[PDB]
Image 1 (cartoon, helix red, strand yellow):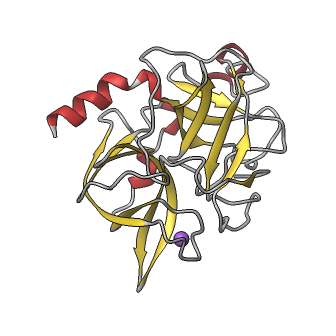
Image 2 (tube, helix red, strand yellow):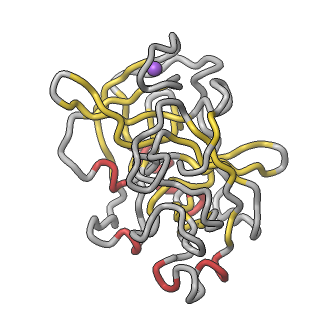
Length: 240
Ligand code: NA
């Protein structure tokens, strides 16, 4: 997250760190959201590589023991069947991961609440992106979980020529684009939290940014719109 601030350690208890085994150690690769005690939602492009993955819940500092972490292996990966890895802009950038064990809920570990199907945010709606991704274009991952305030940019604007044009689809949500704050590498897969009727819900899964840099004016971060996939999610969980 570029232009973020450190999150309080109990602010975003559905956030997870997806990590891969890197020799003797593990390394953060992307974010996700806990949506059942044994299921995680993330971006399809995060699990494109044939790596060994684990999920960490209750994480705050990637480089220190917080006393709150639970570590759990990934048993099954279900990627959206229309996902195509060389066309991120076609959409369907969403995957569900079934965990080997169910995690225990507490003030650091909670299920993400999803929006009702079909729900679309009005332009300029207040939202936060959270994650451990790079803190600057071509920079290094954050140590501690970061948050940034990114108001939504509606489809009519985002899909206009000086923004994203045809690369943004109605199955996506855009937010930010002020040139100071944005998503960045390592934030993929993680949540966009938006406050609606008094309650934060996860409306977006972080999908892509501009190749010209993370925080570029009129290139808002693009998220998979979770409210377009509620039936899909429910069908997967019920059939596995
Ligand atoms: Na830690």
